[PDB]
Image (cartoon, rainbow, N blue to C red; front, side, top):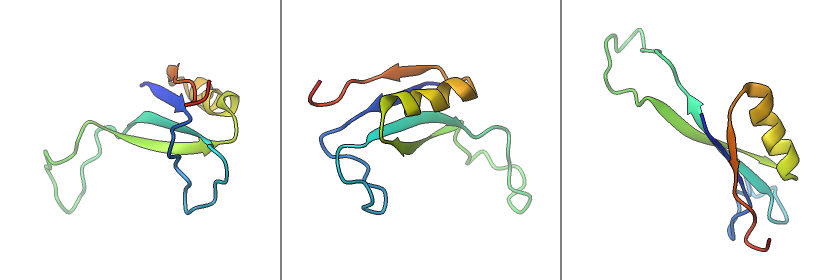
Length: 80
């Protein structure tokens, strides 16, 4: 799974809490073999999903990925 650490021009403010360009961490979030008991056999369940976290530094976003085993690619900010 690949985790991307970046500072975009327009940042994930997350409920409008973030002030400056916060580092967003988007990753291949593994949703494994997990069918719904109501739906039974449901092919309508995509392999993985790309969810995201917000950290004040790159070092905190990569530290997550490393601790989880998620290999990561760093994308430098729009000001690097």
